[PDB]
Image 1 (cartoon, rainbow over the protein chains, first blue to last red):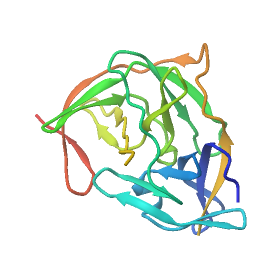
Image 2 (image 1 turned 90 degrees about the vertical axis):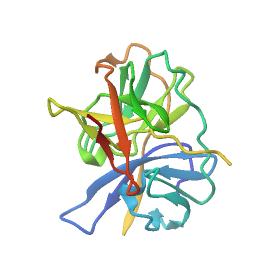
Image 3 (image 1 turned 60 degrees about the vertical axis):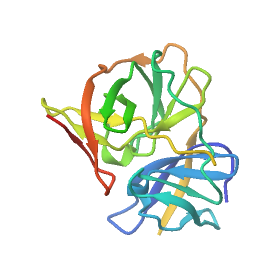
Image 4 (image 1 turned 30 degrees about the vertical axis):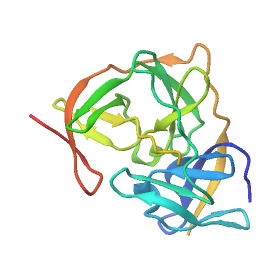
Length: 156
Length: 39
């Protein structure tokens, strides 16, 4: 299968036609997505198979072929870009200043951008093009607007 | 049976569309990975 670094759509033919259920990042031979996109199932890349290697429902993350490789972090001050990959539409960069999720266990950056559920797993990047987390696990606020955490894993 | 298809390179775009606000929210994260608002 295709192992080139970059952003990929995650598709299924189980439903009507070919449906995009999410997005992920290929980096250093490892495929990175959110757990709620694949539910930990194996994936196909052409004639090849990608098996899950690590995952955690609470973090809502999963890696395939190897351990989680993404370790860049939002600096807490600068604008970032969501590299949105919406279903049936071209990859597009959206620049934004993250807000914050304040939790009992610390603060996390959050992006107030609303895309279809199938955009989950799209990468959020810093000005060096490094992936600081994945978009797609968040909350619906007072006025009905969607806000995603910037979800990042740990590089062991 | 899920499959992946390349959609692009991961690169910062100069002069990308700039939007979205920056809300500061108190949230809770449960064991199932669901975020909720704390009021």
